[PDB]
Amino acid sequence: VDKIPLMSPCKMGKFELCHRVVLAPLTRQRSYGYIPQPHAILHYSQRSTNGGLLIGEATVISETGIGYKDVPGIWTKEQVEAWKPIVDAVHAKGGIFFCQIWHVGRVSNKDFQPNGEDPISCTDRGLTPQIMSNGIDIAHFTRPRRLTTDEIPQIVNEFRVAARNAIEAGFDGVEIHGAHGYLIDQFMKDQVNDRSDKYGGSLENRCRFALEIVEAVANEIGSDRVGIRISPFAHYNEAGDTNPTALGLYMVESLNKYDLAYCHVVEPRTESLVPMRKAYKGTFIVAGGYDREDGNRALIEDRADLVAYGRLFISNPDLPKRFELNAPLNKYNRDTFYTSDPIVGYTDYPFLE
Ligand SMILES: Cc1cc2nc3c(=O)[nH]c(=O)nc-3n(C[C@H](O)[C@H](O)[C@H](O)COP(=O)(O)O)c2cc1C
Image (cartoon, rainbow, N blue to C red):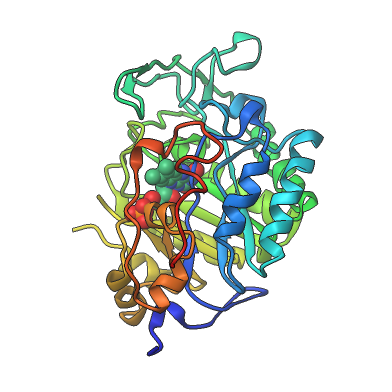
């Protein structure tokens, strides 16, 4: 077997990764009652390799951050203890595990909120209905409540606690969810942020929330245990920006001072991550539409240090091994991406024979 770029070792902060194939954060909606479950142990265990990086599924930081059924949270002792066995199985195979901490902001409904309250956001504009994963049901969203200037720090604090909880759970680090139109991205994107205070207006102001969050977390658990994900070019959840590249450049530049473990950036649908990679001084992770070929290339062309795989890692437990041996890949069934069975479409994808 000839060595390939995707299999090359890599130093990422305090971690010695053995290869560059990363498991991207994947929401599977199989965490009943917002509590991590036993089947997650097998799932993440099936995907752990020695020195391989795994980014866990988006994990809700607080009650108000829920916008989906059965997603895991990390604000209660019950949730923390539930994560431990999952974290242990991953470590048992020598993998590095980061918990993605998340808050949906306006992407929610009052039925998901405590005491039927409205979701919180940088704006009071809500989302139009969207078709769910099955293609039969419609997702309706409640208009959000625009957070006041002095409430925001309270939210910044929620990410902090959560980050702390993740470490108590055993996680090696946390990835801040600054993408896909959720709370943090809502503040960054100008098509959404219509604030008149310091958290809105200019590009510097719109990124303040994010940067305050990065600082709160880095300070709490050490910047070497912190990663952040952004999607400057995505319009997911009606959250675009009239100047993606500047937003992206402003962000990476701004993050250099925090000496993070990495910056995870999502590819577009021109628009390029290259300028961002060039402006960012630390470990750069790219994700979105990659295969084995595109992965080795991006690494060889200096476009990234690590490559995250979503859909392919869903249907291929041994993705790294298959890339290392250039073996065929299992097809993935999107119909069971978000379904709720503990096995079907979650842990029944076969390893190489
Ligand atoms: C079923 C599913 C769940 C996802 N859950 C998350 C999530 O919780 N957090 C996140 O940042 N991205 C999430 N994503 C986006 C992926 O992390 C990744 O960026 C996307 O799959 C692009 O890569 P791919 O072409 O290799 O699948 C999800 C994608 C899918 C298909």
